[PDB]
Length: 212
Length: 203
Ligand SMILES: C[C@@H]1O[C@@H](O[C@@H]2[C@@H](O)[C@@H](O)[C@@H](CO)O[C@H]2O)[C@H](O)[C@H](O)[C@H]1O
Image (cartoon, rainbow over all chains, first blue to last red; front, side, top):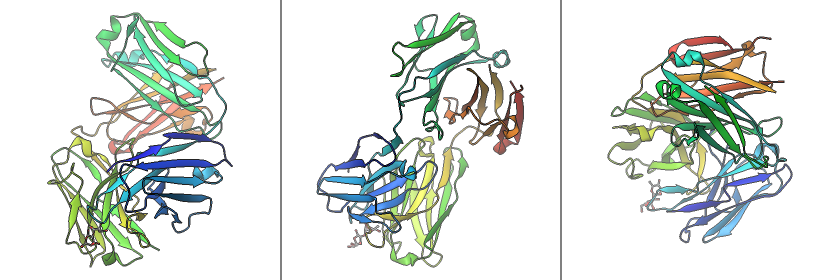
């Protein structure tokens, strides 16, 4: 009925031991299964019956547990083990399968503050009738980052969407884009547009702004 | 050897129907129960339904019963998912999975997945606007549906490029940003197949 995985994210380096776990809501009659999933691909069975390795699964993957607690262990992480892992449960009847909400194994690296950039709406877009303000957070680590939009000091809420890239293959950092959407008439009624960024690599928040 | 191949996904309006197929080879199809498992964007796995090894008994997730019906043809080695009264919440990648040989409560093989997009928006090419260490980029806005490819300087500029995942705006249209940091000319080559839209944008 309910499967809960923890932790939500695991930041390790290649060669380290990864330990993830699933807590079943009730006692489980049918020994859990584990799956590995990489971006854009189908899940692939790793562990079935709690301790058995599916066919073609290297020895470094191990599972154990019984009743309500199960653990998936990767004795030593290889570059290809950085992915998302799901645990799964299923009975004879009712037949529905239930899945854990997933644990992401991510690459550990040193702290790196983002360099911030703010882009005004292009005149081109303004003559289309719309206004998009963009705040870029470039090459930072760790993932956690906070973007706060302000228009003439008015906190903006509900009118921005952000997007984040996967860990860069070279430096292992993340990049995030935040777009503030406004009707252009709205955009034209204001002066100061600012994006304040909070991140562990920064000792004080950084704000990039421009005057219309 | 063992293999599952799906087809049938597509972009559809709400209220319409789609039918998913999953052809199996490499094992005796008639012996195992088969399931459909979906994964909405930015989400985890969410079981959808199953049909017994002999197509006689079916079971559904509550969000789909009365609309979706799962069935099979053991003489064709094909699993189906008839989807009716599709709603926006349904868009996701749908996978077919086989109950395992050693343990039937695990899924040992999965199809590559088939995309189901349900939206009342119609096909539209994007408008590309300029985004002007230093950074610059291109805002590839208001297009439908996915995907769009972005490259810089016909593919000759690659270091420092960050092409962000598309975001679904409240208008039903997608939007994405592609930027590049430079410590020369800069052009984003945007391609949106679904609508034959192509733009080389010099920033
Ligand atoms: C859909 C099907 O549902 C369950 O099948 C079992 C079956 O193995 C028998 O045990 C029957 C009849 O008494 O009970 C059913 O519950 C299992 O979940 C199968 O794996 C599914 O394919």
